[PDB]
Amino acid sequence: DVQPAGSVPIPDGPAQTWIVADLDSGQVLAGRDQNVAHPPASTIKVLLALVALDELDLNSTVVADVADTQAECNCVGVKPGRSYTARQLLDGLLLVSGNDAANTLAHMLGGQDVTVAKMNAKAATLGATSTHATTPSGLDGPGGSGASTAHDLVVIFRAAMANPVFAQITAEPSAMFPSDNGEQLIVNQDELLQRYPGAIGGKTGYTNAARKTFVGAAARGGRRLVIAMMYGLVKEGGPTYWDQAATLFDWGFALNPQASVGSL
């Protein structure tokens, strides 16, 4: 790791790369291999959300087709021939990591290939130049597993948090999603919201190639932090990803505000 001289040693955790940064100033407080590329898994859905929020009206609708509904789970439950709003799909995308929601948003954005090109273009405008999406969902695609870095993930999340709708959604405990029998309540799978006072958003991910990933943010004592963690596996009786995230936030909030190791 790299952390400021004299600071409290950062406890070991499952994440093999990670970064702790200030959401507002862009100061980097600490990092471990924060520029090393690994597959992002579902954390890349945040990048899809940015594109969707830029281009799509929240109340515009799409009729899902069969192709939209054929990716492996997680699924929010998109059904072919049914109508959904961009907002509904974004809730599905961000609360339950719905791959069907991702593919249906990609449908609204002009298709899979076009959506991936738009995501990569968006990463470039943000200076996230170590990021390459291959699918809208973060699933392995024909182009491979894709790539991001802990640094790029917080850069992307920082941009997303600036959007008031994104900030609202990522922090919602629940949302209503269309079903046959009307509407089904879906719950936010981000347990940091429930376990860590001051958490304001987050997105988890897993694939075999990515292992566990996470990006998210919290606010305490007037400061707002953003962290990302990549390429990790939880060992029996070891810290979980939720544990290490809380440990990193706690460490960051306790840090002398003048201390830093670099900037975004």
Image (cartoon, rainbow, N blue to C red):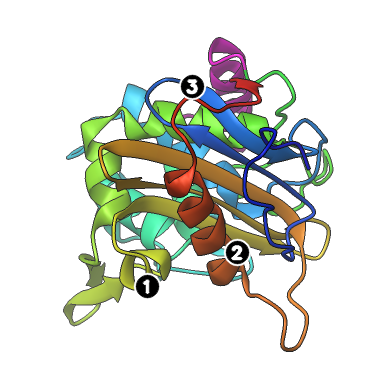
- The secondary structure type at the circle numbered 1 is helix
Q: Kindly check if marks 3 and 2 are in contact, taking CB atoms under 8 A apart as contact.
A: no
Q: Which mark is residue 195?
A: 1
* Mark 2: few/some/many CA within 10 Å (<14, 14-19, 20+): some
The boundaries of the magenta stretch are: 107-127
Badge 3: few (under 14), some or many (20 or more) residues near its Cα, within 10 Å?
some
Residue at left offset 58%, top offset 26%? 260
The amino acid type found where label 1 is placed reads: Arg
Q: Amino acid at mark 3?
A: Gly
Q: Which residue is labeled 3 in the image?
A: 26
Earlier residue among tags 3 and 2 = 3
Residue 155 appears at what percent x and percent y?
54, 27
In the rendered structure, which amino acid carries the disc numbered 2? Answer: Gln
Q: Position of residue 174 (x, y in %)?
A: 23, 68
User: Would you place residue 96 above or below residue 36 in this image?
Assistant: below
Q: Position of residue 220 (x, y in %)?
A: 30, 47
Residue occupied by mark 2: 244
Q: Quadrant of the N terminus?
A: top right
Is residue 144 rendered to the left or right of residue 29?
right
| For residue 154, side relative to residue 52 (left or right) | right
Residue drawn 76% across the image and 88% down it: 236
> Quarter of the image holding residue 44?
top right
Disc with the residue nearer the chain's start (2 vs 1): 1
Label 1–label 3 contact, CB within 8 A: no
Mark 1 → mark 3, Cα distance in angstroms:
25 Å
